[PDB]
Amino acid sequence: VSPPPPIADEPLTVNTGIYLIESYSLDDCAETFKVNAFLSLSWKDRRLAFDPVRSGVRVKTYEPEAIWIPEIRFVNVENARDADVVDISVSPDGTVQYLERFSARVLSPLDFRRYPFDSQTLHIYLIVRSVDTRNIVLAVDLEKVGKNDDVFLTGWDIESFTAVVKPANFALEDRLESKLDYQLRISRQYFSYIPNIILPMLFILFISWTAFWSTSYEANVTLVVSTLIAHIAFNILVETNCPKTPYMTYTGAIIFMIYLFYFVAVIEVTVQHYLKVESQPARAASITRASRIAFPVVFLLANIILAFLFF
Amino acid sequence: VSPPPPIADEPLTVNTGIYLIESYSLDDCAETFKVNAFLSLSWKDRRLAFDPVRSGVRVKTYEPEAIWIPEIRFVNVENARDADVVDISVSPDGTVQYLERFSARVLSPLDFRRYPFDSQTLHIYLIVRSVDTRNIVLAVDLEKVGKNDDVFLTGWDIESFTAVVKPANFALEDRLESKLDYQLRISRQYFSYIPNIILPMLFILFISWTAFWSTSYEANVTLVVSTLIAHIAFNILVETNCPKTPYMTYTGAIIFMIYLFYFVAVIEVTVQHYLKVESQPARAASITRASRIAFPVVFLLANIILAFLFF
Amino acid sequence: VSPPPPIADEPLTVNTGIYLIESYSLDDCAETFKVNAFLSLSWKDRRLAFDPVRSGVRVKTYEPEAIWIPEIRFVNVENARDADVVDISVSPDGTVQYLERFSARVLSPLDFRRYPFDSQTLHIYLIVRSVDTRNIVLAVDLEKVGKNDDVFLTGWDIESFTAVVKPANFALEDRLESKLDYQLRISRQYFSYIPNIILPMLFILFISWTAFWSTSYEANVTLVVSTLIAHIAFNILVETNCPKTPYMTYTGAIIFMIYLFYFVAVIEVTVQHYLKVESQPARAASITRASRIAFPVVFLLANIILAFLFF
Amino acid sequence: VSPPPPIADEPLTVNTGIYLIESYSLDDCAETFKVNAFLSLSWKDRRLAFDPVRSGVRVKTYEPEAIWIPEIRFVNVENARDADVVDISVSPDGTVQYLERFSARVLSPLDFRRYPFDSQTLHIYLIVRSVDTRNIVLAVDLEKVGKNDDVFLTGWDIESFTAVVKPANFALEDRLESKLDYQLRISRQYFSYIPNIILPMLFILFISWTAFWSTSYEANVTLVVSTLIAHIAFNILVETNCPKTPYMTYTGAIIFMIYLFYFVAVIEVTVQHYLKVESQPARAASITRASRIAFPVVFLLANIILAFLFF
Amino acid sequence: VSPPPPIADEPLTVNTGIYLIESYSLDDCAETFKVNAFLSLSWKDRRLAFDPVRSGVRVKTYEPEAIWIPEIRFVNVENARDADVVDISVSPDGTVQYLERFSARVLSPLDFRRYPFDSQTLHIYLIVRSVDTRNIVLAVDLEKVGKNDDVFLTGWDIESFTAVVKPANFALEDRLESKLDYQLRISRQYFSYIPNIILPMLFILFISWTAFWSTSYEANVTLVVSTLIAHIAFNILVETNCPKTPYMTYTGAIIFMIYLFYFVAVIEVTVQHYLKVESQPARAASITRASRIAFPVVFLLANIILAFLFF
Ligand SMILES: [Cl-]
Ligand SMILES: [Cl-]
Ligand SMILES: [Cl-]
Ligand SMILES: [Cl-]
Ligand SMILES: [Cl-]
Ligand code: NA
Ligand code: NA
Ligand code: NA
Ligand code: NA
Ligand code: NA
Ligand SMILES: [Xe]
Ligand SMILES: [Xe]
Ligand SMILES: [Xe]
Ligand SMILES: [Xe]
Ligand SMILES: [Xe]
Ligand SMILES: [Xe]
Ligand SMILES: [Xe]
Ligand SMILES: [Xe]
Ligand SMILES: [Xe]
Ligand SMILES: [Xe]
Ligand SMILES: [Xe]
Ligand SMILES: [Xe]
Ligand SMILES: [Xe]
Ligand SMILES: [Xe]
Ligand SMILES: [Xe]
Ligand SMILES: [Xe]
Ligand SMILES: [Xe]
Ligand SMILES: [Xe]
Ligand SMILES: [Xe]
Ligand SMILES: [Xe]
Ligand SMILES: [Xe]
């Protein structure tokens, strides 16, 4: 078998569609997600056209090996998809209606700059390579693009599953390549983050601030340094232990600031004690009293600046 | 190798049955479970009907490739099941009795709101796509549905394995599809949850409450902050090792409350010391004495409120 | 490609034998072990009998597809075994000497109640489903049941590899199933557990007991609470790395008791200080002096009770 | 299904080309990277020659099984690549133009001496073994070598993808082997390393230096030892998760120096207290005052020496 | 498709050779290593012997299915090797020269008693089972046993790759089996171990010894107990990540001794304080002064004893 001949000079249009059956194993570290879906393909092959009267059948069923089928591949996959041809139906005019069920581990970059208030667009790129006899172009039938109502990703809200109707046609290794962009829009379920991460982290930092209502250097050293240990310990507890980000994230900036605040609070505690020991209790007491307001105010202000910069 | 013809216009009924041989690898983090079972299939194909007299046999055995077999797939699976046809038996009236042994990693959502006192319903969805010449409908042969007595999941009690006899017939990709729901009901058996996680976690919290029978600020700071470190450390030790659930769990609420209590106990310790240092020992001593009763009472009360809200 | 016919009414006997080549990847957490072995099968098919004179050969070699072979499966496996047919030999009377090399991940429950002084019996269940024309029954020749001298599992002593000669014949889905039990007896190598886990864990607990020879509340609080942190930290280090079992283990009871002892020692330290501060140094000194004997004695006694209950 | 015959005695030239579609899963610990690319092959097999006039077609398409294809293997791969033949085109002269899409996990050594300011050259070695009838030699078709613009490796800048045009022809097991070197040059994106790892690690070290403005031995012991705990804790948190490299890395030297500085600061704190207790407050105060300058200066100097030695 | 007949009664000699292409993924915890190599096989079959004058070919090339090939298996493998037949050549005398490229995960026990100053001998056991008509014996072709110069294992020095030329012939399942031992000798690259693990672990222990130049019980308790926490914390950081070995290792003994030393130092600190408080400052001061020498001397001596016992 060889590609169907053109009636004029027109390229062959392969009408696609992807219907999500299952979405699972979204890996934030690897920036990969596992998908189980239907892939529908539709094209016209007049060599396969028939008279339903002199055939006795209104539809003809074929085996994949029996007829010409376009070679559709995915661009952003780990390995080639595991596919199972479900059905191949031919109508009297030569229209081929192909359907397969596939599973694939798709590689899609994730932007964590706004984590855990981030939204992601997961991509699935369909591609077809043209042959010398004729050019092959992809198209989307949006009626055939959908997802099962029970499709889920834990900790995410699945907004929509759509495709960018206009394909990306370009030349590669002296042949035309037609590419389609299938997009799965998801938004993170950030609720439990406040009581599970933020609030306890904030409490530890607030504990370190009680050193501003104490003159005991030994009790102050225990307060700021032991809370720093508790902060690090807490971060180990809730750390995914999975992603080291090249870029600066929102949460990443807050955490860096918290470390800076532990260092500044140590400097204060050190300064206050030194001034007290160096017969200057008026300056020590005035710094400690200022810190009581300065620390929560500078924190609340810098957080507003960060929230503004990232969102 | 075409579907059996209808006697009238009726759809083909494929009688199903699943018998669990082994259940294993239930992953709470991935919301998946590995199953090893028998899949029985029964349908009538009159093209296969024979006279036991002029044949000499009461039953006929066929190879899968020799006869028409419906394409049964699972909806909620990672990849297609690993199947091995055990037996194919045809009776004189054309009744086919198919049996295969399969293994599959099933994706089933889990509700952790009541953990570790939670119960789960694991789902296995059978499906069949109808063909050009006739519609295929699934049915349940209750005689063929069951589980091996030795079937186990560590830390779980297997209540029952049943199927919702009425199939879910709907339209998918312009063809009728009949779906079945097989349910495995399991309840968490975690006898050791109390001694292993709860009690050591409560002991650490109770140690922090000894600061209410002490006036030493240095000893009190060491008590509340060091126990907070011990609490966090203990939670790293008994860590679920599962990514935090988006929703608020029962255990999650108790743990959040424990962090809040560590913060409140710090506030008390800070207030008591400040009042003492600011020549008000009557109000400091009255707060510390109230806390001795207030802390266990508010804890025991809030826990009853939480237990009521979740159960 | 039909089962051999009976001479009278008797069922077909398939003589089995498993010879362990390699045993590896014993996962305590998954309760699974990977095995690489030989599977020998012996049966008589009179349709295969021949005259060695006419044939010119004393033995005949066949391909698996050329002759009838019983469908032997394993009950407690993740997926069907990866098998490679090594040899098929037919003697002039129609006796078949089948041999294959296989690898399989076997699921076998493990009892950790006596850990690390536990012994386990690993099971491999062979099974055959009886066919339409005649019943198939399994048998063992214990001469053919063996293991390579170099077979090993790190941290275990392999006592024996045997089979329960009497098969378990039962009805399942209206047919007979003949099941065989192959047992691998292993006993844990518990020596490094004393210097690596037990002894350092006891030293940490003993350090907390030095608070009974001190009147300094600040030093005592640091002793009991810092050792509790060290205990938890040590447990994180020597993590069994297995999720807590549902049942109460021997080691599990000892560890729970150690947490209880840290709580009791805190109560003592708190009581001592309170009586000392509340003008009662006679009681505080008598309690502390009693604790010096009470704590090691109650510990040593409760440990004897636990060791008695578990063993 | 035999190699093409030589016209004289010349070796067969197989023109190669690799075009990267996707690059992912670069494992620093395993020294491996997963690649998804096109592999183009071109050679002359005159036995496949045809007249485009008699055939009608200007190019002929073949199935891989229909014609002879050179056995190209990769030297540094875990297992043989997962390949999918995209196209096989034969021109009238008998020139074959082969194209396949493959995925492979490539093993390439990584030098971490300059981490996180390191650059790496990832290698892909193509190889062909010569046959009985004729020698096979590899060549590079530069028109067919490249990478997709969207190719990315999280935390890396992809500089270039090139091939060393001159093959390495050598004898192995009495036959000629022609080897090609495909190189992917990458450089690490080290920015978030400063605020995420370096800066919080420096703050903990600086906190330990506040002991040089304190005479309280109890407060000093708490400062240096508690910060050492915080340092270790922080290292557990931002752990590379890679086993210690056999060689001494840049970051490895800095961390070793930080441990040495914690030990030296302890020695100082111990010396200062001993001199004070042994009626020598002039010597104690002069050491502590010197340390205030000595510690940051020696640190800043040794860091310059290390940066010079490694870069 | 029957073994070659013997000229007399001699067994068939299969000359073997393994050439390492790649060595990777050496897992200490799993005691496995992944290998990628060539397997050469040579044997004489006179049924394939031909006259070169009337045939006119250097060597005849065959497909695996076309001729008899001995079934060579590996003893110590997880699953059967992934093999790709590279070449099959037959010379006029009937000498078959077989070559395949394979990948396999080999199970080889590792002795960690001398870690990290250990050397290992990795084993690859070739095996052949004799057949009905004749016995098969393995031999080593030393010209075909080697390794690629670029073969590497991170953290190891690859000394040599050799084979024990004399096979181990024994009876198994009533047939003769000829076994060959291929050995890969490797020695660990222990340099970064001193600055990364040993030296910071000794510094933490040395810090605990500063308690011998202090009379402050509160400062001493903080010294010994906080360093014990730092030691455990450090061990978590540079954790082997391998499950505890059943046997006592060199490093294991040193670490056990370090825990014993922390306990002894606590006893001293406790004894010194008790003697001081129980009006015996002469006895207390003499113990603390002795400990200053006793602790480093006993440590240095016991370490020499351990180093002597293990090496
Ligand atoms: Cl694909
Ligand atoms: Cl399926
Ligand atoms: Cl099986
Ligand atoms: Cl390859
Ligand atoms: Cl093998
Ligand atoms: Na086709
Ligand atoms: Na069929
Ligand atoms: Na057969
Ligand atoms: Na070929
Ligand atoms: Na053969
Ligand atoms: Xe998607
Ligand atoms: Xe955060
Ligand atoms: Xe601040
Ligand atoms: Xe189920
Ligand atoms: Xe909890
Ligand atoms: Xe907190
Ligand atoms: Xe409270
Ligand atoms: Xe077993
Ligand atoms: Xe210890
Ligand atoms: Xe224990
Ligand atoms: Xe506790
Ligand atoms: Xe006790
Ligand atoms: Xe590369
Ligand atoms: Xe910090
Ligand atoms: Xe660093
Ligand atoms: Xe210094
Ligand atoms: Xe090896
Ligand atoms: Xe240190
Ligand atoms: Xe700590
Ligand atoms: Xe060590
Ligand atoms: Xe000692």
Image (cartoon, coloured by chain):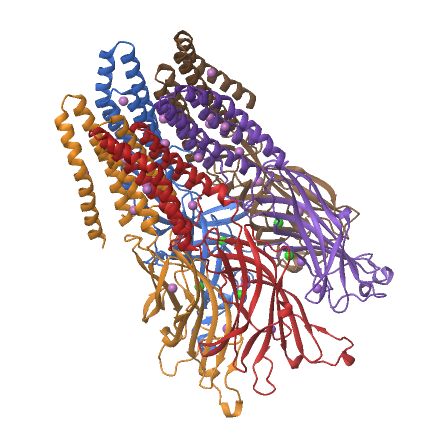
Chain colours: A purple, B brown, C blue, D red, E orange
State the image coordinates of residue E23 (x, y, percent, origin top left). Answer: 42, 62
Q: Quadrant of the C terminus of chain C?
A: top left
Residue visible at 23% across and 25% down?
C297
State the image coordinates of residue B33 (x, y, percent, origin top left). Answer: 54, 42
Instruction: Indicate the quadrant where residue E291 lies.
Output: top left
Q: Is residue C19 above or below residue B112?
A: below
Q: Is residue B174 visible?
A: no
Residue visible at 66% across and 75% down?
D96
Report whether A105 appears left or right of B196.
right
Q: Is residue B130 above or below residue D272?
A: below
Residue visible at 55% across and 36% down?
A251
Q: Nearer the viewer, residue B183 or C150?
A: C150
Q: Nearer the viewer, residue B128 or A274?
A: A274
Instruction: Indicate the quadrant where residue C150 lies.
Output: bottom left
Q: Nearer the viewer, residue E296 or C284?
A: E296
Q: Is residue E98 above or below residue B281?
A: below
Q: Nearer the viewer, residue D290 or B129?
A: D290
Q: Quadrant of the N terminus of chain C?
A: bottom right
State the image coordinates of residue E221 (x, y, percent, origin top left). Answer: 27, 29
